Amino acid sequence: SKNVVIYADGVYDMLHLGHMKQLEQAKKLFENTTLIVGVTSDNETKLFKGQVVQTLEERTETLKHIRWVDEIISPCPWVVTPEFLEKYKIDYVAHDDIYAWLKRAGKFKATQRTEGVSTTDLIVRILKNYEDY
Amino acid sequence: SKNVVIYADGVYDMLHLGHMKQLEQAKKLFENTTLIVGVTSDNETKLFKGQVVQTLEERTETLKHIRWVDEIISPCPWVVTPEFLEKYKIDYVAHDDIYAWLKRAGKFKATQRTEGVSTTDLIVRILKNYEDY
Ligand SMILES: NCc1ccnc(N)c1
Ligand SMILES: NCc1ccnc(N)c1
């Protein structure tokens, strides 16, 4: 089968199993893929989305260790454009509307989030060893 | 170059960049390796070492996403023995003494820990957004 270029993007702050499963899902959308992962900038993430603990460099360095990741664009653009897909020869965007154009182009592929497995969920579990009273 | 079987073991609780760098180091000890990673049991870790947030199954599932990991033994034995090295055809043990026999056998390879990159370090950074006064 021909190689298919998949693009996923995100913050990837305090990388956890939920991120890695979503990256696995994107990587496995077809038999033979290149998974490019875009990591959002510190300034744009904080302005448009919310707070981020780790710097772009830290978030990117951690992602390089994930086996599903073939290429990283860091920083990535905050908004995906058709020209961006042309520049990097991206066939499909893997995502969990602003995205109507992607669906009309046949380039939108859904991925799922996993609940209850985040890094902050783990800290909440640590805290339960300390009773309120 | 002939394939070399490397064994590393650990708790791998709330997997972070420091773990992944140490696994990368073990994987890259020689040109061609198989990196087997042993994950310690919940009961033995808590008895002999200290507290663990994630279950063996969770710690193991997260490790499978790391690109350096070729095989996982989960649970692994708490203490490595010469018979264990024979059973899994392990050439070297990558570790950061109880381990004198490994050094005498020529099978001890040192790896390093990275400071300041742990999951709990990140939570400490979150807390600094809240002044004492
Ligand atoms: N590894 C690429 C990258 C991303 C962000 N900041 C850097 N200094 C480098
Ligand atoms: N994936 C192996 C494994 C380790 C611990 N517990 C399980 N149920 C399974």
Image: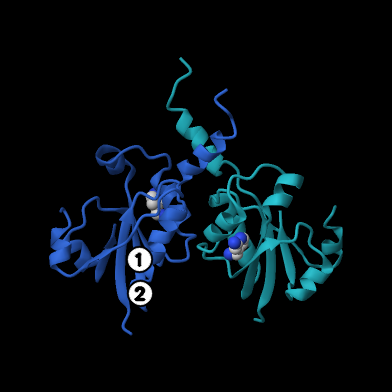
Chain colours: A cyan, B blue
Q: Residue at x 53, y 40 (%)?
A: B125
Give the percent coordinates (x, y) of residue B119: 47, 45
Gap between marks 2 and 1 measured at Cα: 9 Å
Q: Are marks 2 and 1 in contact (CB under 8 Å)?
A: yes
Q: Nearer the viewer, residue A133 or B72?
A: A133
Does label 2 or label 1 sit earlier along the sequence?
1
Residue where numbered disc 1 is placed: B26
Q: Residue at x 67, y 55 (%)?
A: A10
Q: Is residue A41 left or right of residue B89?
A: right
Kind of residue indicated by mark 1 = Ala
Residue where numbered disc 2 is placed: B33
Q: Callout 1: residue from which chain? A: B
| A73 versus B43 height, above or below | below
Label 1's element? helix
Q: Residue at x 46, y 41 (%)?
A: B120
Q: Nearer the viewer, mark 2 or mark 1?
A: 1
Q: Residue at x 55, y 48 (%)?
A: A14
Q: Quadrant of the C terminus of chain B?
A: top right
| B131 versus B126 height, above or below | above
Whether residue B106 can be seen here: yes
Whether residue A28 can be seen here: no
Q: Is residue B48 left or right of residue A76?
A: left
Q: Quadrant of the N terminus of chain B?
A: bottom left
How many residues crowd mark 2 within 10 Å: few (<14), some (14–19), many (20+)? some
